[PDB]
Image (cartoon, rainbow, N blue to C red):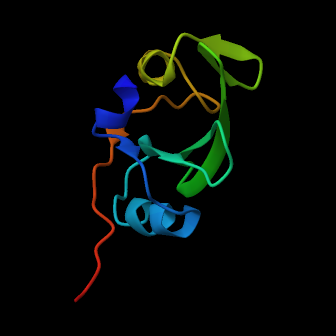
Amino acid sequence: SQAESKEWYHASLTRAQAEHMLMRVPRDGAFLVRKRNEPNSYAISFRAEGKIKHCRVQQEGQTVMLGNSEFDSLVDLISYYEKHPLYRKMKLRYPINEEALEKI
């Protein structure tokens, strides 16, 4: 779907790999979305209050759900949370597009 080509979306990034990337950006609002190793499940990994936090988003047919908040798609969800606070008063602000690198 459309989210898969967005700069904040990572198809193959674990929890720890995501933290490893986010720890290098010293700014609240830094974020990425990663597919989880369970069907129809994604995580938003983000920086808030100086920490890294993870929240889960479920794909539910034609829609996605974050807690009790429904959106048309992952792209619409992220757009909404760039405009409205996701966590306390903090909005998503800095999409992280880093590659998890394999040293060879």
Residue plotted at (43% across, 44% down): 31
Q: Position of residue 44 (x, y in %)?
A: 55, 42
- Residue 98 as seen in the image, left or right of residue 90: left
Residue plotted at (65% across, 17% down): 61
Image vertical order of residue 21 relative to residue 34, above or below: below
Most distant residue in the right direction? 68
Q: Quadrant of residue 20?
A: bottom left
Image vertical order of residue 52 relative to residue 30, above or below: below
- Which sits in the foreground, 34 or 28? 34
Residue plotted at (68% across, 49% down): 38
- Which sits in the foreground, 28 or 82? 82
Which quarter of the rendered picture does the C terminus lie within? Answer: bottom left
- Which sits in the foreground, 9 or 19? 9
Most distant residue in the left direction? 104
Q: Quadrant of residue 95?
A: top left
Q: Position of residue 10 (x, y in %)?
A: 40, 49
- Residue 16 as seen in the image, left or right of residue 99: right
Q: Position of residue 35 (x, y in %)?
A: 53, 46
